[PDB]
C-alpha cells in the first residue's frame, strides 16, 4: 500500500470522512485519487477553512480534518487556531510541505521550520522524518487532537511522501482506541460529594467543556438535586445549560470584583468545564466562599488563582456527580423573570428588538452564533436556548469565527436551523466564507447587525475616557452586495416590519440567506 | 508582604522545604533571608544539582525545587532535564534573571529568551510579566510539575522582583489542592475488567510510572489474581515489581521483533505505566495478541504503534484493577530459576560476580542505581529487589544521572542503604556530585565498575562491525583520587577477596564511600 | 559516494580536520571509518567537549567541529553554548539522532524536537528531512557558523543517514567560499573619518571582536594616529589591545553611571567590536559625548541604548580606519603607571601577588584564561599582555569555560604557554576536562586560586547587605587529588616561596600541570 492509501484508511477507520481545505501544489499528491467515500469542503481563505471545520467539530463533538497549503496557508489560519485553542476544538490541521529534496535549498513553497509556525496555538506540531512515518504521525495527530483536553494539532507533510510505500505494520494503527473518559477515584469523589451535600448555599458555574461533553443534561440534574443556582462562566464560547431553567442565573460578569461579589454568600462554588476565570477589564473570592473546579485541562487547573481543582473528563465527572449527590430538601430556585421589552419605533432596530424577534420566530431547536460584540449581554438574556449545542462565540475573542463556524455547525446539524448574529465590523474578517454556504447549499442564516461602527471598541474607549482613537468606524459597506457577490440570497431590514418579513422569508428559504439589519448607533 | 515572603510561604504550604541549587548573583535576592525551616543543598555543577533533586523527587514521590543561575546554569542542567522528561520527574526548576531594567540592553548574566531555553524538555516554561505575578507563576509551576503526567517545569525570575510588594490576594494560592487521581469510568472499566477475566493467557508489562505511583503492591495482587507473567518494559528507569516474585519474568528485550515474539501466544497484554515501547536498535505484535495500555501520559498513548490506550492515573487504575478482577483458577506462574554463578578467578572481577556479591551482602531494603551500561541485563537478573523504589536508571539514557541521583535518593530515604553501580566512563559526567555527599554526610555507596573503556559502545560498534571508531577508551583515571579530592572515603577492589572486604567496610561506614572495582575488559 | 564520505570531504575541503566529541550509539555510523587525516579529541563531559572546541576556535580564529550524543549530550553542553553565543564563537555542533524509522515511536536515545533544544543559543539549528540532504545541511552549518557575526550552530543527523548514497551534485558544496569581509561604503566612511579627524578629545573602546578579527595591530595604529586613550569594553571575553601601550587605559567599569562618567569630556567615543555595553549591577552618556559603534552583530547595533552604529566586519573596518585617519598633532597619551606591589607575608597569597609573580615568570607570549571571579580587576592591571589572543574569560559569565577552553587554546597555540587562572569554585564545573589535557599531553598550566569560597558571590551579597544567603562556601576540595585522579601532575603553593618554586617547575614541565594556590579569604 502507498502512504496515501494507508493514510486515508487510517482516517476512515478513525471516523474521519470530510476534509476542509484550500488546495495548493504541495497538497496535490494527497488530494489526488480522492476517495469516493470522502467529502471535500472548499473555502476561499484559510481562516474560513478552519472556522468552518471548527464549527463542524464543536457541533459534531468529533475531530475535524483540515488541509492547508504550506506556510502562507497555515499562517492565514493562525487567528482561527487561536479561537480553537481556547475552545478545546479537536482540529487535525495538515499542511503540505515541499518535496524533501527541495526543502534544504528553500525552493518556493517551502514551509521553513514548519512545526514552529503554528506554536504556541497547538497541542502538538510535527513534521515526519520520512515518508513511511506519515501514517504513524497522522495517528499521533488524530489522538492528540481527540484526547482531553481536546485541541488543535499540526502535521506538515512533504509533497513526495504520499506516493511512497507504506509500512505494512501501519495496519496496527487503524483501530486504535484511546480513552480519556476518566473521573476522580471513588474515595476522593465520595469526599467531594459529601462536601456538596453539606453545602448550605451552593452555587454552580458551568463552562464550554460541559456543552462539548454533552454533559448539559447531567448538569441540570445536578443543579436540581443540589437546588443550586447556575451561572455560565464569563467570556462564554458555548451554552452549557437551558437558559429558561428555574436554576439558570445567566452569564457572569467578566470582572474579578464582580464575580467575587456574585459568589459572596455561597459557601461552596462548584465550577465545571470552565477556566477559573476568563476575566476581562478586587478580591478573587470573599471570605466564606470555597471554590472547587472540575476541568479537563491541566493548564486551567494550574493557573486558577484560587480554589481546589480536579483534572478529569467533564462528561464522566458530571454524570458521576449528578447521580451520587443527595436530593436537597432546600427549595428549588425560581426562574429568572423574562427580560423587559425595549421601546422600539418604526426606525432603526435596537438589538434588544432583534433578539426578541429571533426568539419569537426561530425554531425551538435553533442554534445561534454570536459575533455582535456590543450586544452579547442582551443576546444571552433574550434567547431561550433549551437544548445543548445552541450557542457559539469566538473562544479567544478572535473575530472572523462566527460566519464560517455557522456554516460548519449547519453542516454538522442539518436538521437544526443555524442563525449567526454578526456585527458589521466582524462580518468582514471572514466574509469569503459566504461562498462555501452558497456552493454546498448549506442553509445558514446570517443576521448582520449594521450600526456602522466597531461598537464594543467605542464603548470601551468611552469607559476609559480615551479620546482621539482612530479606526473605530466602518461606514460604507453593502452586505447585500457582498452576499450577492458570493451567491447568497440577501435581504435588508431597516425596521421591525422589514425584520419580521425578512426572517419569515429566511426561515422558509431553501438555501443560505443573509439579512442586513440597520441597528441603532452607539 | 514581599514577593520573597509570599513565595516561600507558598512553597512551604505546598509541601516544599528544600532547595537544590548552585547560586549566582541573579538569585541572591531570592536566597537571602533564607527561611530557617528551609534547607539548601549545594552542588558544584548544575547537572549535579538537578540530578540530586531528581533522585530526591523520584524516591520521595513529591516535587523537588531547584534554583539555578541564569542561562549558563540552566544550560548546564539541560542534559539532566532530558532524563527528567522521560522519567516524569516532578522538578520545579527556577533560574534567576537580570533585573528588569537590564534585560533589554542585555547586560551580563541576562537570560535571553529564557523560557525557550529549556524547551522542549519541560511541561511548562515561563517568565512572569511583573513582580507581583511571581507567586501566581510559582503556583502554576508547582501544579504543572505535580499533575499527571508529572514532569519538569521552568520559571525564570528577574533579580529585582523578590523585594517588591506581593498582592495580598496571593494568599488564595497557598492551600490550593489539585488532583489528577482519576481512573476510567465505571462502564468502560467494567468492560476492561471483563476482557482481563476472559483472557486465556494474559501477560502484564509494567513501566516506571507504577513505581512512581507506588502501585507495585497493587500490581502484584493483579498479577496473582490473573495468574499472569509480568515483565518490565524495556529501557527501564525504575523497578515496578518484586524481582523474585513467582510471576516475575524480568526485563524485556528492547527490540521490536524481540518483544513481539516474547508476547506471542498471549491473547491479552496489559501494559501499565510504560511507553509502548521504549525500543532500541519486525512486527509490533503477532496475530492473536491484543494490547491494552494504561498510561498517565497522553503523549505515550498517542505514539504507541499498536493497541488500545487509557490515559489515567496509574495508582488509581492499578488499585481499581487489582480489586475488581476475578481470581483466575489458572495455576500461578512458577518463579524463574536463580541465575548461574559465573566462573571467577582471583583476578579482575566479572560484573556477574559483583552483582552476586552485592546481592549477598546488601540489606534486603537496599536501593540500587545503575549507570554501568554494558552490565544492565546481568544486574536485573542478579539483584533481588523485593521493595518498591529499589532501582533507578537514567530514563533518557543520559549519563551523569546515577551519581548525583544516588545522593538525592539517599537523602530521601535515610533508612535505606543506597548503592550506585556506575561504570568508569559514566562516573565522570557528574563526578563533582561526590562533594555534596561528603559535605552533607549523605552515606551513599558508589561502586565504580572500572574496565577502562566505554564498554557498551564497543559492543554496539562490534555488532555493527563498525571499524576505526575513535574515542571509545577512557584509560588513566584514578577514582580513589577523585573521591579523595571531594572528601569521600575511597577503597579499591582488584579481586573478589578485596571486593568483599571493601563492601563489608562500606556497609559499616558512617559516611559516603566510593569503591573502585577492577572489572574484566570487553 | 556515501553521505559519510561526502560529508568528511566537505569538512576537509572547508578546512576542518578535527572533531571534538563525546561519543554515543547515534554517532557511531558517523565516527566509524574515521578518516586518517582527521583527529578526534575526546572529553569526558559535553560541557568540556564544547569548552575545549570553543578555546580552539577562538584561538585559531576558525570554526571548530563538535560531535555530541542526542539530547542528553546536547543538553549537557548548553551552558557552554551560552558562552559561545556571547563570544561569537564559530562552533559547528552536530548531534546524532535515532534512525529515522525509530523517531516517531520515540525509541530510547531519540532527540525529540531536536532543533528547538539548543535555541535560543544558536544562529541556526536544523535536522535534515532526508539522508541525501545531510551534506547540504552541513554546508549550511559551516557557513552559518563562519559568517559575521560568527556563532554556534546545531545540526541533528539521524543514525541511518550516513551509509546512504549521497547526491553527486553535492560536489558543488566542497569549494564554496563565502565572504562577509565588508566595510562601510566610501562616501559614509569618509564622513566617519572626518568626524574622527575633527574630534578634540576622542576616546576608543574595544571589544572581543577586535581580538577575534586580529584587528589588534590596526587598532593600535588607529589609537596612535588619533592620539586617543583606549579602554576595553566591560565584561571582556578577550584582550583587544596591548595592556602596556601608552594609550591603554584598562578595563572599563561595568556600571552605566561609571561608564558615562569615564567617557565624560570626550566629544567622540569610537567603540569597535563590542556590545554597547555589557553592563552589570544613571545616564548612558553625559552631554557633549557622541558615540559611534562599529559592530559585526546587528543584534548589538539594535539594542545599544545610545549612539550611531555601523554593522560591518571588524577586521575590514579597523584596517580601513587605521589607514584613512590623519595623524593628530595632539600629544600621544602617556602610559599608565605600574600597579602597586601589595604587602605580602609568608602566609596565604594575595591574588595581587599571584598575578605579579605570573607576570614576572611567564613568557612574554603567554596566553592567560580567567575564571577567578573576584580577582578580575587585579588580573587586568597586573599582567602585561603585549600580543593578540592573550586573554579569555567566559563571555556569558558561565563558569566551567576556562578549564576546558585553556586546553583548546593550548592545542591551537602549541608554541605559546597557556596559563589558566581559575578559582576553587569555578574549577569544579568542568573538572573532568583535566583528563583530556593528560591524555593528549596538552601542556596547559592550571593555577587554582583556592580561598574556600565563592568569593565574588560573598562580595556581591556584601554590597547588597544581603544576610543569611546559603551555599556560598566550598570547603573540603583537594585539587591535587583531583588532578592526580585525571593524570595531571600536581603541585601546591601555600606561600610565595612555594608559588615561585611551583611555577618554575610548571614552566619547565613537559605535560599539563595543576598548581593549587592557597589564597587569602574574603
Ligand atoms: C481578529 C480580531 N481583530 C480585531 C479585534 C478587536 N475587536 C473589534 C474590532 C471589535 C468590534 C467588532 O465590531 P462589530 O461591528 O462586529 O460589533 P459591535 O458594533 O457590536 O461591537 S470587538 C473586538 O475585540 C478582534 N477581537 N479580533
Ligand atoms: C551524556 C551522555 N553522553 C554520551 C553517551 C553515550 N554513551 C556512552 C559514552 C556509553 C559508555 C558508558 O561507559 P561506562 O564505562 O559507564 O559503562 P560500560 O563500560 O559498562 O559501557 S553508554 C552510552 O550511551 C550518553 N548516553 N550520555
Ligand atoms: C555555570 C554558573 N553557575 C553559577 C554561577 C554563579 N557564580 C559563582 C558561583 C561565582 C563564584 C566563583 O567562585 P570562584 O571560587 O571560582 O572565584 P572567586 O572566589 O574569585 O569568586 S561567580 C558567579 O557568577 C555562574 N556564573 N556560572
Ligand atoms: Ca458594529
Ligand atoms: Ca566501562
Ligand atoms: Ca574562591
Image (spheres, coloured by chain):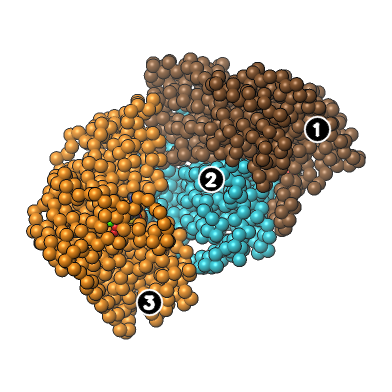
Chain colours: A orange, B cyan, C brown
Circle 3 marks a residue in which chain?
A
At x 64% / y 39%, what residue is drawn? C278
Which of the 4 quarters of the picture holds residue A258? Answer: bottom left
Residue B463 is at least partly visible in this image: yes
Residue at image point 63% right, 38% down = C277
Disc 2 packing (10 Å; few <14; some 14–19; many ≥20): many
Q: Point out the frontmost of discs 3 and 1.
A: 1
Labels 2 and 3 in the same subunit: no
Q: Are marks 2 and 1 in contact (CB under 8 Å)?
A: no
**Foreground of the two, C324 or A193:** C324
Give the left or right position of residue A254, taking residue C180 as reference: left
Residue receiving disc 3: A202
Which numbered disc, 2 or 3, marks the residue closer to the eye? 2
The quarter of the displayed image where residue A208 is located: bottom left
Asked whether, in this view, residue C403 is left or right of residue A189, the answer is right
CA–CA distance in space, label 2 to label 1 = 37 Å
- Chain of the residue displaying label 2: B
The answer to whether tags 3 and 1 share a subunit is no
- Number of numbered discs visible in the structure rendering: 3
Residue C55 x/y as whole percent? 64, 28
Residue A467, numbered circle: none
- The Cα atoms of the two marked residues, 2 and 3, are separated by 43 Å
Mark 3–mark 1 Cα distance, whole angstroms, equals 76 Å
Q: Which mark is residue B114?
A: 2
Residue C70 spot, x, y in % from top left: 49, 36
The answer to whether residue B496 is visible is no
Quarter, ligand 1: bottom left
Image disc number at residue C382: 1
Amino acid at each position: 500500500a502507498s502512504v496515501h492509501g494507508t493514510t486515508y484508511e487510517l482516517l476512515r477507520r478513525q471516523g474521519i470522512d470530510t476534509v476542509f481545505g484550500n488546495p495548493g501544489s504541495n497538497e496535490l499528491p494527497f488530494l489526488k485519487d480522492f476517495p469516493e467515500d470522502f467529502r471535500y469542503i472548499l473555502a476561499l481563505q484559510e481562516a474560513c477553512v478552519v472556522g468552518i471545520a471548527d464549527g463542524y467539530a464543536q457541533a459534531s463533538r468529533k475531530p475535524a480534518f483540515i488541509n492547508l497549503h504550506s506556510a502562507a496557508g497555515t499562517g492565514n489560519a493562525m487567528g482561527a487556531l487561536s479561537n480553537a485553542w481556547n475552545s478545546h476544538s479537536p482540529l487535525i490541521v495538515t499542511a503540505g510541505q515541499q518535496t524533501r529534496a527541495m526543502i534544504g535549498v528553500e525552493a518556493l513553497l517551502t514551509n521553513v521550520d514548519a512545526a514552529n509556525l503554528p506554536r504556541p496555538l497547538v497541542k502538538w506540531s510535527y513534521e515526519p522524518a520520512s515518508a513511511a512515518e506519515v501514517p504513524h504521525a497522522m495517528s499521533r495527530a488524530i489522538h492528540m487532537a481527540s484526547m482531553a483536553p481536546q485541541g488543535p494539532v499540526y502535521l506538515s507533510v512533504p509533497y513526495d511522501d504520499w506516493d511512497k510505500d507504506a509500512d505494512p505494520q501501519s495496519h496496527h494503527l487503524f483501530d486504535r482506541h484511546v480513552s480519556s473518559s476518566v473521573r476522580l477515584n471513588d474515595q476522593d469523589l465520595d469526599i467531594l460529594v459529601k462536601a456538596l451535600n453539606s453545602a448550605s448555599n451552593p452555587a454552580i458555574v458551568l463552562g464550554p467543556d460541559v456543552d462539548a461533553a454533552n454533559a448539559n443534561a447531567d448538569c441540570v440534574m445536578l443543579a436540581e438535586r443540589l437546588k443550586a443556582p447556575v451561572w455560565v462562566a464569563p467570556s462564554a464560547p458555548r451554552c452549557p445549560f437551558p437558559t429558561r431553567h428555574p436554576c439558570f442565573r445567566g452569564l457572569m460578569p467578566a470582572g474579578i470584583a464582580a464575580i467575587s461579589q456574585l459568589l459572596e454568600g455561597h459557601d461552596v462554588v462548584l465550577v465545571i468545564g470552565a477556566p477559573v476565570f476568563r476575566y476581562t477589564q478586587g478580591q478573587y473570592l470573599k471570605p466564606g466562599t470555597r471554590l472547587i473546579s472540575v476541568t479537563c485541562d491541566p493548564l486551567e487547573a494550574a493557573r486558577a488563582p484560587m480554589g481546589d481543582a480536579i483534572v478529569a473528563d467533564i462528561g464522566a465527572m458530571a454524570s458521576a456527580l449528578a447521580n451520587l449527590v443527595e436530593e436537597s430538601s432546600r427549595q428549588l430556585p425560581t426562574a429568572a423573570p423574562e427580560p423587559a421589552k425595549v421601546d422600539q419605533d418604526a426606525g432603526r432596530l435596537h438589538p434588544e428588538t432583534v433578539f426578541d424577534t429571533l426568539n419569537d420566530m426561530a425554531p425551538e431547536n435553533a442554534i445561534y452564533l454570536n459575533e455582535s460584540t456590543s450586544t452579547t449581554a442582551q443576546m444571552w438574556q433574550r434567547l431561550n436556548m433549551r437544548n445543548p449545542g445552541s450557542y457559539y462565540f469566538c473562544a479567544a475573542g478572535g473575530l472572523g469565527f462566527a460566519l464560517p463556524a455557522a456554516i460548519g455547525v449547519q453542516l454538522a446539524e442539518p436538521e437544526r436551523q443555524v442563525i449567526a448574529v454578526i456585527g458589521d465590523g466582524s462580518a468582514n474578517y471572514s466574509i469569503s466564507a459566504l461562498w462555501t454556504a452558497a456552493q454546498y447549499n448549506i442553509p445558514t442564516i446570517f443576521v448582520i447587525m449594521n450600526n456602522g461602527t466597531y461598537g464594543a471598541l467605542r464603548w470601551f474607549a468611552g469607559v476609559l475616557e480615551a479620546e482621539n482613537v482612530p479606526g473605530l468606524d466602518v461606514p460604507g459597506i453593502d452586505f447585500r452586495a457582498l452576499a450577492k457577490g458570493y451567491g447568497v440570497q440577501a435581504l435588508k431590514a431597516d425596521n421591525l416590519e422589514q425584520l419580521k418579513g425578512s426572517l419569515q422569508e429566511a426561515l422558509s428559504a431553501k438555501g443560505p440567506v443573509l439579512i442586513e439589519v440597520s441597528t441603532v448607533s452607539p
